[PDB]
Image (cartoon, rainbow, N blue to C red):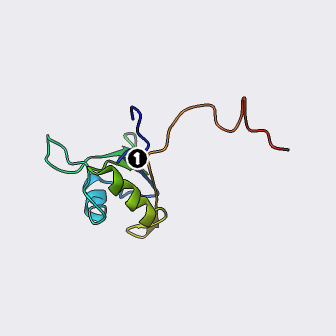
Amino acid sequence: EQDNSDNNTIFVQGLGENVTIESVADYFKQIGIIKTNKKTGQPMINLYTDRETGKLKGEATVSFDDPPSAKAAIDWFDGKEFSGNPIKVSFATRRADFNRGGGNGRGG
């Protein structure tokens, strides 16, 4: 964020009732260092869990202490498996409107 395309922050999708911080920190600590927190002194990852049923969603973003390390990870994981399931590691894509439709896009 704030003028940065190599955002160490990555995006992991495809967990499955296993999207945890330590789980991601445990398996995503070989390629590089995970964004450790100053409160718990441990890696920091954003995960989406359910509150109505009390389960997980299966999607979470992992923060990295080294921007270049995030890319190197994507080069490897980008379609890896989480305890059996498949995942998709990215370079923290942008979330917003205006995509493939508007001013540009032509091509005929």
Q: Amino acid at mark 1?
A: Asp
Please tell me which residue is depicted at 81% across the width and 43% down the height of the picture: 107
Tally the numbered discs: 1
Horizontal relation, residue 93 to residue 83: left or right: right
- Residue 46 in picture, x, y percent from top left: 34, 44
Above or below residue 22? Residue 100 is: above
Name the element at disc 1: loop
Q: Where the N terminus falls, by quadrant?
A: top left
Relative to residue 24, is residue 60 drawn left or right?
A: right
At 35% across and 54% down in the image, what residue appears? 68
Q: Is residue 57 visible?
A: no
Query: Hey, which quadrant is residue 92 in on the image?
Result: top left
Between 28 and 85, the one nearer to me in the picture: 28
In the image, what residue occupies the spot 37% across and 68% down?
A: 83
From the top left corner, tell me how far across and down residue 108 is, in percent: 86, 44
Neighbor class of circle 1 (other Cα within 10 Å; few <14, some 14-19, many 20+) is: some
- Closer to us: 20 or 3: 3
Q: Is residue 105 left or right of residue 62?
A: right
Please say if 21 is above or below 3: below
Give residue 16's position: percent from left, percent from top: 42, 58
